[PDB]
Length: 148
Length: 144
Image (cartoon, helix red, strand yellow):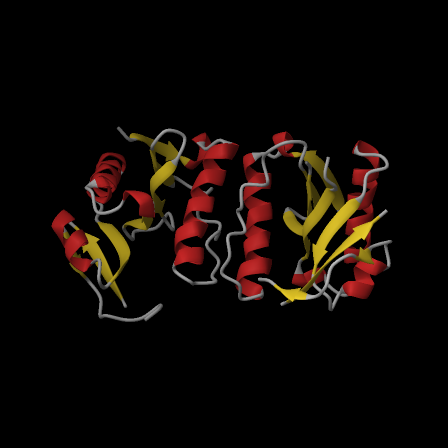
């Protein structure tokens, strides 16, 4: 019984912001062994939204949506997370479809781009994405994908 | 150089993003360490954050943790643009003045390394620990 929140960045409280960067750090920095700049600015600007999956005051799912650069290019999905205690069990499919329902609602008549791993390709292709890119590397494999 | 001294309840959404952003930019990308900087110590108890501002850009940072056990200093940062000229010595000057004000006659502990030993030692800190590696030579000093 995960509650979902589709937050424009202006609605984020201090504890809501803390929870999603801490979970982003825990997954993309710590567990994925990648010292990088996870906190890049793109979170509190423009019409950008965040989607949070909560399981009893625990943030167990997250994705952010970039609408930029206030230019022609598509909707960007990124930072897609399920917390490791809860994986292999339909929640990732729930996060994605609700995040596309957000892309669909807010900006219909705009496709959705998404940067991904190579090994995650068949899971995003089950949501309507197709590779728009050659396989390349950020840690030892990425493909660029887009929907509609 | 505007300085702020905020109990964690006074952090706005923008002040919270900025100090984590600089902390990630110093302790994880620059020092090449993939650790959990956002560690759950920032928004609890009487813990406070000391900020130094210059043109809508956080350039000096330190953190103060509470709880029967001593007051702790950590996360000490001078952004690279401003390093090497007096910004660090005076950050911990607010930061020890801040301890001395809320917790008067209460001993400051500072987790540090070693290379900068003489730096922190210039403010009253004393080795309490033996050197060990962490995430990287370390030592735990203390003041008063």
